[PDB]
Image 1: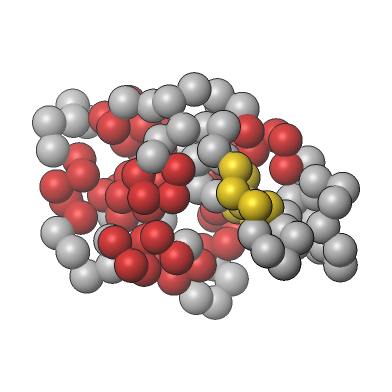
Image 2 (image 1 turned 60 degrees about the vertical axis):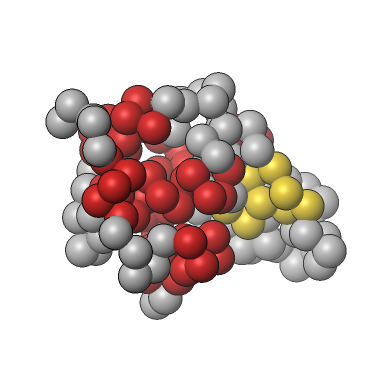
Length: 129
């Protein structure tokens, strides 16, 4: 499923992400834009044999099990294929764990590079919420 920007912004607000750990909704919509471009099925293979899954590109080495990553931890306690559904609930619940894991939203590289320190409120413009 490819989300519309305000469509995803409402979904994320509904799942408790606005000001979650002090990160406004715009941060989360921006991170999803530059991680997956709002595509729930986005996957990126990394050279270390891990793969990043879903709208927030969560990694198979530590957070979800995809059965092909050596030395994987399955911290969110899910199959990685569950991060690839049109329902964003599994990805949002695992992201809540990752943002509280000691690096805040620095865990997402595309957010550090394209959202950190910017006017992230632009990402919610025109959204009815």
